[PDB]
Image 1 (cartoon, rainbow, N blue to C red):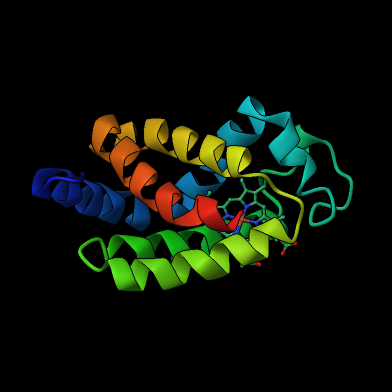
Image 2 (image 1 turned 180 degrees about the vertical axis):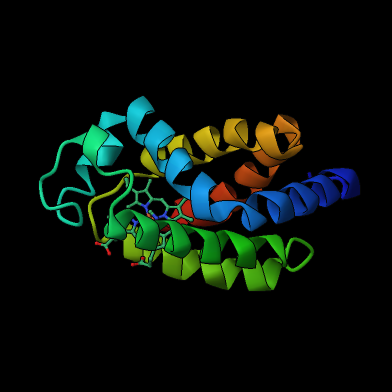
Length: 142
Ligand code: HEM
Ligand SMILES: [C-]#N
């Protein structure tokens, strides 16, 4: 279950982080990489083997941030549309699975995102529920 209140909170807070994504996106990745080394490992190719505390201001980081943001924005705009959600989720999972990434790792990411969102007026509880509904749709395909 997702209440109307949780959905409104997720949409408003995302709007705010979205306007600041130019600088916050990279901060989000750094926290993620700091919390899970296994996650950073999967980006070795994109980063060309560079060490973790060295990727923040790279052109690849900027690009990766914009990619992350475009999918999250689509999920957010369709919270009352399970059908739409399902389809976006299918592609996302097929793509990530093919890289050897686990359901557990995806889950890890959503947790760091929920905490991160607190800085933008986000209710951690509302982000956590949104993450569970999406995981319910991703898992069967992982
Ligand atoms: C859970 C929230 C996530 C979102 C919204 C997200 C979103 C995306 C999107 C939109 C793309 C580009 C389309 C594609 O190539 O699939 C992508 C690519 C990628 N993702 Fe994610 N992803 C997430 C989680 C992860 C995690 C946890 C990892 C690592 C364990 C990961 C690793 C990658 C890599 C390696 C690529 C390809 C980068 C390249 O172009 O070389 N993603 N992700
Ligand atoms: C990773 N997006």
